[PDB]
Image (cartoon, rainbow over all chains, first blue to last red; front, side, top):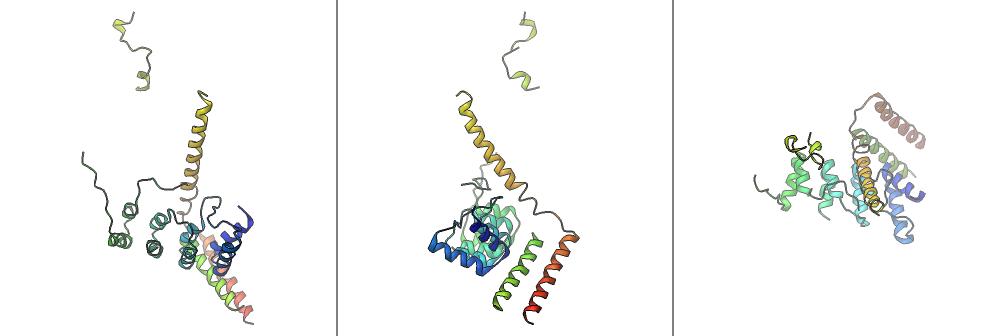
Amino acid sequence: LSTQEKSYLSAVEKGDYASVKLALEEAEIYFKININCIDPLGRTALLIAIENENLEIIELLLSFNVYVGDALLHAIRKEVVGAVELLLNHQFSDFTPDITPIILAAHTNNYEIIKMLVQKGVSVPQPHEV
Amino acid sequence: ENFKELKQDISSFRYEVIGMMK
Amino acid sequence: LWMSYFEEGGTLPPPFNIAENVRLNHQYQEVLRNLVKRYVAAMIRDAKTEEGLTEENFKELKQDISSFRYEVIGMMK
């Protein structure tokens, strides 16, 4: 984890919009740092910007086509409505390979997200009774 | 998490204003 | 009680009674690495952000505003 990545992650964590944009611009032309990097606990830039609900940072990081991965599940578990709206209209995992967006949304009684998901059309598989 | 949210709001506000006056 | 009946030692009531490892350490180490990573991510990073608030948090949040105000006032003068 280079220092040029520690500076970038710190800028994302505080909320310095101009600095994060400058780092992203200097990355696409010099290819120095890897935007898909992990900090010691394992977070990426997307997770850091979602954990603080920084909608401007989240929108910016989508305009540079970062890796999304299980970023929708994290927003659903954190119950961030704006982040879910953004992520919808666009290897180590923390979730079991059987958890889908609608299931994980239904575990949390959040009416807004559940309605937002079922408006797009989903389906939960009924298990055969015994 | 609420405390970190409320601290980050102030941080981003400060950065934006400082950059706006310079 | 159950484990006492998993082996072929007694297997018979009293009336009628008278590398192979080094390869596996690879899989075991891979499994431990995944388990430790999951535990760190789940317990000591994702359940520390669910504690309560005290007076130190309030003083922190007040001092942030104080320093911001001082800096801006000095910047406009």
